[PDB]
Image (cartoon, rainbow, N blue to C red; front, side):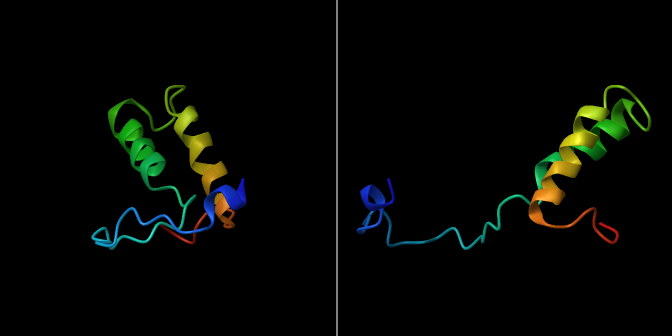
Length: 69
């Protein structure tokens, strides 16, 4: 539970991975989507999985589709 966590950790001081992680977004699943498109999609039955995954992402993130990205 929360209190099981929030004391301190003291795992890593050297916070080398200067890479903020907003969560949701849709990076990998977009990349997978456009990759599926490129391979054998445009329309196809084989891309719908990634197209669906592409929306839930952004809906959750809080944008019902981007402007253009």
